[PDB]
Amino acid sequence: RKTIDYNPSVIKYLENRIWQRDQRDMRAIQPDAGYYNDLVPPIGMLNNPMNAVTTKFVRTSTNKVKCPVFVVRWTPEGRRLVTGASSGEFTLWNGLTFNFETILQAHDSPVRAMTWSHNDMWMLTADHGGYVKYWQSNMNNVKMFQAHKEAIREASFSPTDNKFATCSDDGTVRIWDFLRCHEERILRGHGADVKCVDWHPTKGLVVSGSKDSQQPIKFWDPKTGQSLATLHAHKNTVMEVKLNLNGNWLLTASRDHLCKLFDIRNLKEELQVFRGHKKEATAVAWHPVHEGLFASGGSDGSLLFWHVGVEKEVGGMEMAHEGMIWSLAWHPLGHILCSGSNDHTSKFWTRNRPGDKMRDRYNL
Amino acid sequence: MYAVYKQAHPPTGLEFSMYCNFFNNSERNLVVAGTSQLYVYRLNRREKLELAASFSFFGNVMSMASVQLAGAKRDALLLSFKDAKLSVVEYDPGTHDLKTLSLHYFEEPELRDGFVQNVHTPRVRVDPDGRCAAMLVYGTRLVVLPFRSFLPSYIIDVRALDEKLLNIIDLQFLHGYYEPTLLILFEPNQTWPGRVAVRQDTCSIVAISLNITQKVHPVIWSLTSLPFDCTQALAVPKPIGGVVVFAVNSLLYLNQSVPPYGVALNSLTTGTTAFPLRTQEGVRITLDCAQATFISYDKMVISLKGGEIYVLTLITDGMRSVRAFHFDKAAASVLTTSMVTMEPGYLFLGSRLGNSLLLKYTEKLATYSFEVCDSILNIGPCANAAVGEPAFLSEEFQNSPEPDLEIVVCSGHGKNGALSVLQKSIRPQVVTTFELPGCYDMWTVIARRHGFLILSREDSTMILQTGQEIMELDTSGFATQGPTVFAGNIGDNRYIVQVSPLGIRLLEGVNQLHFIPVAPIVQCAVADPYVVIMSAEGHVTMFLLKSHRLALHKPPLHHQSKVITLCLYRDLSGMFTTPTHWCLLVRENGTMEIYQLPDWRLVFLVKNFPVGQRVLVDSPLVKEVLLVALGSRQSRPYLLVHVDQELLIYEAFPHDGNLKVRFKKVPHNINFRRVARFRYFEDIYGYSGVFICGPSPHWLLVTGRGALRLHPMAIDGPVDSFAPFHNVNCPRGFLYFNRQGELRISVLPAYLSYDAPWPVRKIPLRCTAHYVAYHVESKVYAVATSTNTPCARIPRMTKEFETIERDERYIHPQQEAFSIQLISPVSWEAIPNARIELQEWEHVTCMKTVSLRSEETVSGLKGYVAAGTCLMQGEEVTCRGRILIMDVIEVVPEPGQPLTKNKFKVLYEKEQKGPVTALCHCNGHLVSAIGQKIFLWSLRASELTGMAFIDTQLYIHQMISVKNFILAADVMKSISLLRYQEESKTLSLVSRDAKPLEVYSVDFMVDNAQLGFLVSDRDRNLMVYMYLPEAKESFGGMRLLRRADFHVGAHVNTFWRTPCRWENKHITWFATLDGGIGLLLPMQEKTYRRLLMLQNALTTMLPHHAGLNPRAFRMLHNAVRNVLDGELLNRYLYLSTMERSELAKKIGTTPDIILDDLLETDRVTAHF
Amino acid sequence: MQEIIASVDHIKFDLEIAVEQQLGAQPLPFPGMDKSGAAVCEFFLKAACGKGGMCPFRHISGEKTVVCKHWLRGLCKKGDQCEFLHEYDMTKMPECYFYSKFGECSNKECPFLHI
RNA sequence: AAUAAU
Ligand SMILES: [Zn+2]
Ligand SMILES: [Zn+2]
Ligand SMILES: [Zn+2]
């Protein structure tokens, strides 16, 4: 059966590292079928982000419960992919052969958030009922409490994991203390459902995307609870608010078929807009290694790969996935990408292999 | 916590080359630069390169170019450093250094457009007309630097041209245009070799006319259908004009007024290029990583991947419209990183991963044949190092406490892959030792074989007649009633002169001609036919060989101040202008005065010589001075002066009736903390130079390469005297006295080349050396090597296989076949029939010598050799590995081959449950990372039983243990820390770095009680972690906290520790991936803090090459700078005494204390 | 060869001292946790830990024989109270279900004991 | 034994 192993590519890259100082010494991989061993992980080919446009299809991972997948997340080491379905199930799939391992019952209500702490230790979640739970790397629940009284749509850890922020349909963003599990402050002011929250990598911001057209995106202060700024970016219902790990850009994705790259340092000037989604853009995933490259999951199922600086899309698979995509998670190496879908399924995509007539149904 | 970084071996391996007018406009020079070094070479006509000048930068060069600015007398150098730095440097006569003309910073945060990770290197270009310049900064900004010497530059937002240029591949300055025209090869819509069915051909070329005055840059001659795989582009010279694009499987010629002309090379372009391409005949190659250059307007030389050299001709009609191409496979050569056509008939093939060699071509009787004239030694990428003890050590030196070691490196790659047997010091092969008491000074004369040997005692003098048998004499012919002050060869190795306090005697051999009576003589130097003797009160007398018979001629000298020393010189190569004889001289007041011997007119003067100025220009307590010509035909003189237990050595360069010469000091690491101290040997194993006696003996060698080399003789302690030797039983060799009065007849070991900075031997394996391990029992090295073979099968899964069948114009991928050799230290030749041939695709991921426990040996450990392999068959075939534990045994040697007494014994080999990506031992166990886990096995008789396994990360690739703690390392995530409790078979994670990091290697920084984990980074950073459970950032030791930081200028992949020659601290040596070797020596808080002040003063109040900053260079990638910079701190020793005192008083410490702190870091770092 | 020139057996390290005394080890929160991969308590083995249930490290008992098959996979929730052995000794592994009941063992890399 | 083979 299919088995995408990154060990050959990591060993080849470890071999090349010794005598190749950059890409300028990398011998050209040729578009021939007999060049299977010339690949390296995206870490090797760094100034050609084109390689990690994962358009090859590996396998479709489905459960026997058949419930829509609202969140997919890779274990910090990549050993397995966890899948938060709409029934509370935590299906775990292998990280090398993408095969079923174990199915749990974490939450009574649909899972909507799943964030692995900035260290491997902890894995927060959240469900439609507002409950928040703590998990260990052995999938053992450690503590549970009700954070909000309405469905939590996202939860994001701080640079140091002592605090995390959550957003609910109640229209407020709350900031909690990790160990004490006690709310600190309610960041009120949006006035309607909040659909995303992302804690800035370092500076300690809390951005949020809301369903209200008046203040679609707001900037908060974790400590004082103020409202540092407001942004009228999109027309309606910002679906995903993600921050780049470099701490400069904020990429949104709204229900107006658009994704906009913003510079947090300069909110007055719109930096870039990504046209090309035929329907609502409901998912985003920055690349773990390539800063600038990201995927995008439309509400029509389309899956597009973008880059910062290029006017047009780098290249994706329209109709990559039935239903509407909910979340996308790159493998920690970056050579695989799992896409959650409203169609009770998730799919694994990997980089193309040199020397293939790209006649697949997701390609041509 | 605290440390100091010292550099042991300077990086080897060039990166850029050019043939410019560096020194003057008359003769051109080859300027080659590595990473942080610049070398200016010459050509001496056998054709041998000669080094002219070398300079070190506080940065890593990323490009190089030259310009003949308006009105200049030289060629300016447009160096470029990382993150948009442009430095225009120039040679400086009168200081023999690189002065700086204009340094441009472009590190504004708004120029990067919000990209933190920079993956683009600056690329500097110039017009062939010398009118302009450019620089591609961050891959989107183009710094146009107009030339009239400079004009206010400006920045072109390349993304805001008439057409936005993205993913620029290569840019060149074109020929034969009215305004500086720039070609841009770029990909508006990037693609990947593995994704070419939806983006077939994505490339373009655009030419923009740079209007300097009006700052307008229109667009002309755009093309938009080039094949996607376009690696570079070259501008054809003026007579033809245009540009050639070097596609991977194609070659194009483009001009604006004519249609394109492209020819394919190999039939891998059938469906990957819709560009109209011909089919080249009789050629199948790949221009993917290939240097190139133009012999003339018509022919260019290409050096592909693999080193093959071609000579392409641009067949053209009378209209100069290129009509056809013509290749021909000329003589193959090294893997080249650069190339430049030096002379009309010469070429240079620079290389980093292999020796860089100069060529020479001649017409065949349209067709050329390439020979080789010279090569540059290159310790290529140091993949590994296995410290071991030298096979041969003299039984005389076997009784020393300090260990004697050597390091064997896996240098080079591919056809140039080899091993490098690096050593630091000189180890004489003592042939015979004579216990002679009292005598301290000696001289070996010639009567070429050394007929005699004169020894000096307190009261008497005995002479040894060397030859068939060395035996003391008893008859007349020499003075024996008193000590001898000098005895050497006058005439031409045909007469004997010995100097005694009562006079000077001239001997024809055994017999004596006559005695010339004469403040007892204290020093004498002879330059044939001139003999000069200096008395105790400073008097100087001159003697000439007037026919033979020495003649008296009192030199006319006005002694304003007494003469303290004096030296005699005889220049054969004309550099002391206005053979000739010069009498260097040092006066009491501090003035040095080169004189003229035939006449005696003053010819030089320096006001304060003992101070140690970094350059000497015309108009304390110096003890000995020696000026001697070193190099080919004795071309470049050097001045060596011994002042105040400190050695400073001046070079010599010319500069315009006083002497048209000047002397410049050269860096140094020798601390000296009447018997001469500088001994000149003309031929010792084919080498010429000076031996520097005293507390730290050192050997000064410089070959026809002209580069100075200093080598220590630490073994046997200090050296009193020294002398060259050539006997029937003893070939060209030396003879020195020991501190214990032990005369030692010696000969230099013949298997080492003392031309490199460190005595090295290159063992060409002709394959890729991957690992190396030393087995302590049987004292032999193992080596893992790989050779490339065409791949004719594609592994698949269902196992099955598919055969690769194509047409005759097909390029076969290079599959790697692995094998483990066994290199005998005795002769450095692989052991026949002792080789392990691994499976077809098995790639040796790791190999180390492992001390598994055993009961047969008296100790608790045995010391087998352990390896871990892995079947690489693409990302679709499951990856599995094998642990191979081999023991080297002894067998009765086969007659005629004494080296076949060793043979690998395969105790264990089994297919594990995953790739064996790393290996190590812990207190007699075997720890191995098999996939997502680390196991811990116990050595049974012939099996391995598992003890304790834990899950770590994606890919562990480097493990190491101390007593019970295992320091794993991940390719992406971080280092870890695991602890084995022996009482209960449990492996526990003590701590773990919480931040992502691309690690290269790991080791241990060992202090008395605290233990730091030295880690190497992809970005060339060295940092030390710690496990401190009582800090706040680390909750209970859960996090590892960085306590030191340093940005080394090179990638480091291997470490090893050696105790300081400091109670319980160990040095942590490393070898960088560009041929360098450095240290990391721990230090005390007081020492570090009192040397940080000196470091800050050096950074601030000193001018640096190219105007760079030392402090900014060493900042990591937040920064905790607890590692001093021994390379920058070394410049404090370079400074004069006056500047040292000024800087010391400025920072608030005394110069003597600062020196004591600086010199101990060299005393305790004199291993190997 | 590394242990001959530079030996680390006569040096008492601050790291050794720290891990010996469980220095700076704050009691873990949420009594219901497992904390797999943690060393065994060096104090509970001699007299007593004094932080029963709250100990950062592991408290062991000499009763279990069969190796926990879930611990091998890396997901067992019982942890410190696991009713099955928690070491890599591959001689008390569970008997192969397919071999014992459903004929033979389909996979040739099975670690479960065959009887 | 809690999904070892979904
Ligand atoms: Zn305890
Ligand atoms: Zn268990
Ligand atoms: Zn079985």
Image: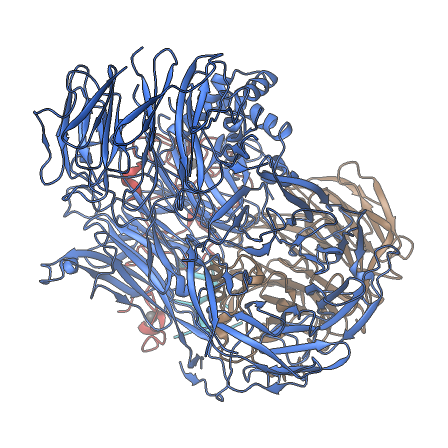
Chain colours: A brown, B blue, C red, D cyan
**Residue at far bottom of view:** B807
Across and down, in percent, residue B117 comes to: 66, 52
Side (left or right) of B407 relative to B1112:
left
Residue at position x 46%, y 55% from top?
C76
Which is nearer the eye, B218 or B67? Answer: B67
Q: Is residue B254 above or below residue B913?
A: below
When the figure is inspected, residue B832 is found, relative to residue B479, above or below; the finding is: below
The relative height of residue B1095 versus residue B972 in the rendered view (above or below) is above
Query: In terms of depth relative to the viewer, which is nearer, A13 or B47?
Result: B47
The residue closer to the viewer here, B822 or C76, is: B822
Q: Position of residue A335 (x, y in %)?
A: 58, 65
Question: Residue B891 is drawn in which quadrant?
Answer: bottom left
Image point (50%, 83%), residue name: B810
Task: Judge left or right: residue B431 versus residue A327.
Answer: left
Q: Is residue C82 visible?
A: yes
Where does the image place residue B58, in percent across and percent down from the top left?
58, 40
Q: Is residue B1080 visible?
A: no
B743 on left or right of A233: left
Q: Quadrant of residue A29?
A: bottom right
Residue B531 placed where, x, y %? 33, 26
Report the quarter where the C terminus of chain B lies: top left
Depth check: B179 or A294 in front?
B179
Residue drawn at point x = 65 percent, y = 68 percent:
B234
The residue positioned 48% from the left and 56% from the top of the image is B352
Q: In this view, does B139 lie to the left or right of A59?
A: right
